[PDB]
């Protein structure tokens, strides 16, 4: 157990637990400090830390000490005895809180027992030397006014009050002659400057601070956790493992980059959470090795120590026993000490990954910042930590008896205001970057708001070094984790070995290095005319002395005029916001503009499914103009083209080492040592893949995800500026009214702010999801593949290396040089899939990853789309696409492959995508339109198979071919074994749903089957179990290849590939998404057009067509003529028959050239009667359910309706459309739908039934039925002449 002593500042010095100490940095000169032993080996000196600081620097100035901290200054802190005593009692309370739980009690026990080794690097291995400043500190015994009598004591930790900056807590180690005992295995007296009352404030981006933009946001820290964070540094320093290694260094070559001190791995380890992941596995092992090497030096010292010259009273055995336990060394029955690898590993992991701020916070139910790399806010002052009503030893601020335990409400600034006070801004100093234009207006930007982008020098290149493989050689992995529960239950973690007495000889060698600090300018001026994130955010603000502003979509005007505020919301939103109204209409206007605000903000939920993008925030570019000028043009389009990359302010140069070669050592005549070597080399190979992935993750988190974090914060600020601006306008307009008017105005400012705030919260959630998706996308498509390329290269090099090794030892391997030959091929065959959870256990990051992998669209590895008269891959993997001259392309994303040799597309796929999952798993989807057979060429049509898409490599791959009315999918494995599955449509149907009509094809492949889906429905299936490996990343050639007719062609659209098997559900969804359009379509599936001649088809009367009756102004219905020749393979009904209709636009006299017909358009349905254009009319006064339509010349009669509304009542994909007659555009009076009706005719000569072109009210209720009735006689399709259909 840990005992925390009690005392008052004025208690008498007793030279034991209350002393006059001579601090290490005093160099044995100057004055002494009254110090209090709070626990064994730990001292508290309730006075400001002044070592290395100028007295005046304790005042706020035009300078700052740290570039990444909102620095608070207060020279009066601790300037009285009562203030010093309060500091003392507060420290006692914090220590009691720390030991209130086993985890914290153990941290203290480890620290108390982690006594510094007696000596350092300069001390002979045979000796213990206490006469060094890192081991002994002196206390003055003599009476006041004379340093006549001094006594030495051993100490572990000395905690002082703060230095100039109250909120800048720091743990300091002792350097002597340029070396640090605490960094070389020995450990040394540790010092700390700490302030309990002025604590840091933080706010989680992904989480709302009580969700109130008009209230105080964020949470304040529990000083006990802040102290434990420092105590962890103390722990590391005491065990001598606070080693230095390759640090994370910020790139500062660009003006938008955050400047900061180099960050050592030890600091990131101390924080925990995701931060250890920024330290590559290479560096993790580097640090591990250095610490182990340091301990070896200590264990050697224990085996050689014979005496202590500095203090004859030191019992050598007692210390050897204590140090053996401290470092967890093992000792044999003879007393020989050695390192136990298991015990060392456990100790190391416990100290680096067990005791972390994140783990401690979690255990103590204390909320803390999400990461070391999270913006810093202004600190606050805790009113009274000694008041149990506000802060307790057991629960800190989150007191359950006050219902503040839930959701860390006790630390919530918006909720627990009674616990703290805001700090006077006049006492705060912050490093700012003054961005000046070349003229010249300037904008100040806190350095903390800039992008933190780790420089390339931050990462280890150890992966490029060679590795000697031996029967020995084993894997090397360091799990940046340690089960906190076992640590809390570990029975032998805490020492039960006697702590030596602290009294020793007085220190006489005061040699020590004392740091010297100095402020630097708080403002750095730079010149740039760039208008990026900082400038855009700035344009959305207004000075405090202005109260009348107006919104503008002009960024430039917003910068020029103080009364103009930039807004990235719609033109209509902006206009309405600037509208001035009468008091009587003010309440209405407020409701309107506030509602508009929510609508605008909610556009952050916009979907873009047709472009294979589930979510996109269209206004991010306009809001920040971050990255590659995202404020220009249409952001959504730009995103569809370049993806996440366009949002990055800077594209990082990644470190992706050429993996060093392996050196396989041979063992002649040794069958085992040779086999072992081969195996070890294989396992080491995987370590290489893992370490590379870890190197990628570290860079992604410190150079990319950091930039996206800044963008998320930027959008939060942007949205708030918009709400603040609207709030300002509303206030101004309301205050223009008189008191009498105001009294009659029904407005609730809190309800307004509530609605605005809620809108922002909804938007932020979408924005965070969007940005996290972008971050993972960059990782997977722009980083991982580049690493895979090197790893695959490495594999190849290692492959022949191993085979050539199995060759050189062929003899010594006898009848096995083949068994292990394949053992190498099959091992280097299956590559390691990237799993983020392997490099981090951070829930946020893991969830981001899993979410990404759960989105089927992220499985797209090829997406050929039209953009600027060319076809490019928008999958994000950058396939090279060569479209040759003979390929016809249009903006409807359709492309035509003809019989010409130059009508082809060459696609070179990305070779670094996990495609060969080792069992075949991928899908291909596309739309196609295959022309009808030539009647005089039917034999060749059914006989000649021709390839249309071929993807082969090493005589293995896949291809899509066509043989007449059959489309074929074929797979060929490395052995040449072939399997096919096909879809063949009937060519004897009166009316075919497939011939010359666009239809959707989807082919899926898995370990068992090959399936072909047509328009979302499964059509064919082939068992492909026997098929072995199939290379599918070869070049893809789109070209008609075979014995084809010169007239042969094929149209294709939306070609894409998925590296997974699509489900029937995925396919059906894709079919509907790609079928969707605002416009109606024609019989063939193309957009329906105005001013284009069409024959009419009736889905409910397939073989019927319309003809103007010779003797009457009506359309009689006749039977389609049919294929006349004698071929046994074909049959169809003629399509180019009946009246030639033409659709004309109703309004806008923009002439009659042509255009696209959209659902709900009002039209005129006309047709040609010889040299005249006639029209389809409905007699206005029929009383029956239906009537024959009236066909006559164009004219305007008061007795006939002439306006039709084209409709689409079917919710599912169809090329059918309906035609409605309404009394007039305005009314909701429906006359009926155009269809076909059967009439009975009994004349003097003939008696029979005849069908006529009619309008009927009966259809009105029928089109509402579900599922939509495709057989209804009111379903029509328009057939224009098409080269793909001849008769
Ligand atoms: Ca790491
Ligand atoms: Ca302005
Ligand atoms: Zn730290």
Image: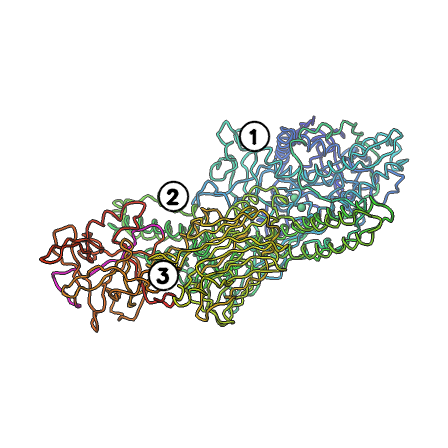
Earlier residue among tags 3 and 1 = 1
Helix, strand or loop at mark 2: helix
162, 1224: nearer the viewer: 1224
| Rendering quarter of residue 758 | top left
Q: Quadrant of residue 978?
A: bottom right
Name of the residue lying farthest toward the left:
1244
**Which residue is farthest bottom?**
1171
> In the rendered image, is residue 139 in sight?
no
Query: What is the quadrant of the N terminus in the image?
Result: top right
Residue of label 3: 1084
User: Where in the figure is residue 170, as x and y percent of width and height?
Assistant: 66, 44
Q: Residues within 10 Å of mark 3 (few under 14, many from 20)?
A: many
Task: Mark 2 and mark 1 in contact? Answer it, CB < 8 Å.
Answer: no
Secondary structure character of the magenta stretch overall: loop
Task: Residue 642: give x, y in percent of width and height.
Answer: 51, 60
In the picture of the structure, the residue carrying the numbered disc 2 is 754
Badge 1 crowding class, 10 Å Cα cut-off, few under 14, some 14 to 19, many 20 or more, is some
Q: Nearer the viewer, mark 3 or mark 2?
A: 3
Task: Tell me the mark number nearer the camera, choosing from 3 and 1.
Answer: 3
Q: Can you identify the residue that label 1 sits on?
A: 395
Residues at marks 3 and 1, CA–CA distance in whole angstroms: 72 Å
Q: Is residue 1205 magenta?
A: yes
Magenta stretch containing residue 563, yes or no? no
Which residues fall within the magenta stretch? 1193-1212
- Dot 3 and dot 2 residues touching (CB under 8 Å): no
1252 horizontally vs 458: left or right: left
Secondary structure type for disc 1: loop
Instruction: Measuring from the top left, give residue 763's x and y in whole percent.
Output: 43, 48
Q: Position of residue 489 (x, y in %)?
A: 67, 28
Q: Residues within 10 Å of mark 2 (few under 14, many from 20)?
A: some
Quadrant housing the C terminus: bottom left
First in sequence, mark 2 or 1: give its number.
1
């Amino acid at each position: 157990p840990v005992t925390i002593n009690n005392f008052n500042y004025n208690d008498p010095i007793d030279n034991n637990n209350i002393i006059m100490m001579e601090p290490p940095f005093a160099r044995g000169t100057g004055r002494y400090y009254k110090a209090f032993k709070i626990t064994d080996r730990i001292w508290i000196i309730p006075e400001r830390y002044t070592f290395g600081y100028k007295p005046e620097d304790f005042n706020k100035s035009s300078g700052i000490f740290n570039r990444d901290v909102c620095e608070y200054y207060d020279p009066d802190y601790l300037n009285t005895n009562d203030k010093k005593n309060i500091f003392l009692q507060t420290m006692i309370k914090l220590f009691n809180r720390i030991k209130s739980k086993p985890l914290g009690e153990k941290l203290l026990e480890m620290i108390i027992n982690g006594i510094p080794y007696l000596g350092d690097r300069r001390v002979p291995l045979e000796e213990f030397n206490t006469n060094i400043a890192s081991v002994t500190v002196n206390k003055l015994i003599s009476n006041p006014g004379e340093v006549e009598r001094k006594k030495g004591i051993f100490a572990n930790l000395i905690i002082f009050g703060p230095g100039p900056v109250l909120n800048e807590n720091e743990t300091i180690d002792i350097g002597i002659q340029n070396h640090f005992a605490s960094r070389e295995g020995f450990g040394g007296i540790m010092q700390m400057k700490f302030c309990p009352e002025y604590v840091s404030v933080f706010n989680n981006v992904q989480e709302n601070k009580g969700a109130s933009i008009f209230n105080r946001r964020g949470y304040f820290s529990d000083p006990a956790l802040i102290l434990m964070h420092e105590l962890i540094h103390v722990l590391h320093g005491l065990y001598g493992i606070k080693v230095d290694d390759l640090p994370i260094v910020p790139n500062e070559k660009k003006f938008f980059m955050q400047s900061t001190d180099a960050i050592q791995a030890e600091e990131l380890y101390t924080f925990g959470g995701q931060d250890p992941s920024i330290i590559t596995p290479s560096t993790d092992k580097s640090i591990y090795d250095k610490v182990l090497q340091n301990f070896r030096g200590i264990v050697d010292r224990l085996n050689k120590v014979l005496v202590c010259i500095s203090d004859p009273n030191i019992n050598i055995n007692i210390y050897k026993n204590k140090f053996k336990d401290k470092y967890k060394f093992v000792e044999d029955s003879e007393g020989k000490y050695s390192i136990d690898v298991e015990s060392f590993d456990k100790l190391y992991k416990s100290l680096m990954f067990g005791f972390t701020e994140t783990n401690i916070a979690e255990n103590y139910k204390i909320k803390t910042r999400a990461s070391y790399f999270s913006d810093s806010l202004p600190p606050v002052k805790i009113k009274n930590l000694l008041d149990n009503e506000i802060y307790t030893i057991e629960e800190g601020f989150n007191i359950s008896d006050k219902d503040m335990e839930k959701e860390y409400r006790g630390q919530n600034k918006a909720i627990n205001k009674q616990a703290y006070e805001e700090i006077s801004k006049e006492h705060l100093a912050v490093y700012k970057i003054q961005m000046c234009k070349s003229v010249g207006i300037c904008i100040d930007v806190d350095n903390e708001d800039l992008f933190f982008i780790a420089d390339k020098n931050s990462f280890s290149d150890d992966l490029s070094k060679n590795e000697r493989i031996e029967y020995n050689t084993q894997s090397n992995y360091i799990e940046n984790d340690f089960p906190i529960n076992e640590l809390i239950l570990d029975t032998d973690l805490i020492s039960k070995i006697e702590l030596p007495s602290e009294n020793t000889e007085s220190l006489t060698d005061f040699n020590v290095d004392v740091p010297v600090y100095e402020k630097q300018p708080a403002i750095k001026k730079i010149f740039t005319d760039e208008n990026t994130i900082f400038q855009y955010l700035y344009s959305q603000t207004f000075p405090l002395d202005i109260r009348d502003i107006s919104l503008t979509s002009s960024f430039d005007d917003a910068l020029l005029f103080s009364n103009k505020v930039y807004s990235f919301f719609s033109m209509d939103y902006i206009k309405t916001a600037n509208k001035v109204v009468e008091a009587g209409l003010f309440a209405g206007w407020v409701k309107q503009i506030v509602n508009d605000f929510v609508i605008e903000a909610n556009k952050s939920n916009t979907m873009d499914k047709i472009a294979d993008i589930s979510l996109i925030v269209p206004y991010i570019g306009l809001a920040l103009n971050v990255g590659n000028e995202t404020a220009k043009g249409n952001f959504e389009n730009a995103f569809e083209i370049a993806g996440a990359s366009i949002l990055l302010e800077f594209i990082p140069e990644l470190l992706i080492p050429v993996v060093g070669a392996f050196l396989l050592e041979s063992y002649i005549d040794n069958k085992n040592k040779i086999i072992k070597t081969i195996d070890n080399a294989l396992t080491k190979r995987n370590e290489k893949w893992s370490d590379m992935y870890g190197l990628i993750v570290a860079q992604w988190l410190s150079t990319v995800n950091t930039q996206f974090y800044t963008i998320k914060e930027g959008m939060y600020k942007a949205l708030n500026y918009q709400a603040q601006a609207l709030e300002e306008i509303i206030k101004y307009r309301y205050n223009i009214y008189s008191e009498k008017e105001k009294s009659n105005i029904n407005i609730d400012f809190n309800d307004i702010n509530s609605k605005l705030n809620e809108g922002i919260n909804q938007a932020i959630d979408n924005i965070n999801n969007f940005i996290n998706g972008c971050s993972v996308s960059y990782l997977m498509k722009k980083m991982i593949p580049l690493a895979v390329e090197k790893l695959l290269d490495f594999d190849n090099t290692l492959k022949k290396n191993l085979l050539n090794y199995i060759d050189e030892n062929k003899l010594y391997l006898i009848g096995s040089a083949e068994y292990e030959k394949s053992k190498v091929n099959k091992y280097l065959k299956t590559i390691m899939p990237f799993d983020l959870s392997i490099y981090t256990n951070d829930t946020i990051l893991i969830e981001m990853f899993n979410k990404y992998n759960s989105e089927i669209l992220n499985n797209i590895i090829l997406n050929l789309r039209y953009k600027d008269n060319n076809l490019i891959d928008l999958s994000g993997y950058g396939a090279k696409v060569e479209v040759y001259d003979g390929v016809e392309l249009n903006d409807k994303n359709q492309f035509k492959l003809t019989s010409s040799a130059n009508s082809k597309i060459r696609v070179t796929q990305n070779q670094n995508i996990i495609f060969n999952s080792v069992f075949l798993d991928f899908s291909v989807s596309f739309w196609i339109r295959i022309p009808k057979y030539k009647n005089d060429g039917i034999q060749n049509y059914i006989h000649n198979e021709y390839t249309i898409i071929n993807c082969m490599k090493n005589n293995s791959g896949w291809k899509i071919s066509i043989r007449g009315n059959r489309i074929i999918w074929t797979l060929i494995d490395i052995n040449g074994k072939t399997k096919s599955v096909f879809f063949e449509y009937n060519i004897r149907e009166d009316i075919s749903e497939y011939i010359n009509r666009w239809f959707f094809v989807t082919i899926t492949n898995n370990l068992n089957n090959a399936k072909i889906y047509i328009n979302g429905k499964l059509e064919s299936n082939t068992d492909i179990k026997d098929i072995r490996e199939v290379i599918a990343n070869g070049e893809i050639i789109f070209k008609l290849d075979g014995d084809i007719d010169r007239t042969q062609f094929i149209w294709m659209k939306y070609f894409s590939i998925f590296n997974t098997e699509l489900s029937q559900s995925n396919i059906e969804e894709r079919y509907k998404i790609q079928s969707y359009s605002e416009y109606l379509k024609d019989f063939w599936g193309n957009p329906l057009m105005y001013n284009k001649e069409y024959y009419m088809f009736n889905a409910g009367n397939k073989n019927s067509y319309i003809k103007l009756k010779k003797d009457s102004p009506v359309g009689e219905i006749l039977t389609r003529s049919k294929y006349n020749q004698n071929s046994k393979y074909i049959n169809y009904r003629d399509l180019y028959i009946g009246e030639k209709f033409i659709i004309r636009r109703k309004s806008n006299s923009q002439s009659i050239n042509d255009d696209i017909v959209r659902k709900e358009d009002y039209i005129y349905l006309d047709f040609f009667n010889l040299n005249q254009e006639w029209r389809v009319y409905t007699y206005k006064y029929f009383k029956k359910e239906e009537e024959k339509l009236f066909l006559a010349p164009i004219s305007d009669s008061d007795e006939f309706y002439n306006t039709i509304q084209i409709k689409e009542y079917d919710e599912q994909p169809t090329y059918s459309c309906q035609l409605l007659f309404k009394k007039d555009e305005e009314s909701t009076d429906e006359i009926g739908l155009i269809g076909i009706h059967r009439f009975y005719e009994s004349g003097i000569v003939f008696e029979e039934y005849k069908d006529y072109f009619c309008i009927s009210k009966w259809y009105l209720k029928e089109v509402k039925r579900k599922p939509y009735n495709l057989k209804l006689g009111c379903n029509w399709q328009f057939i224009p002449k098409d080269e793909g259909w001849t008769e």
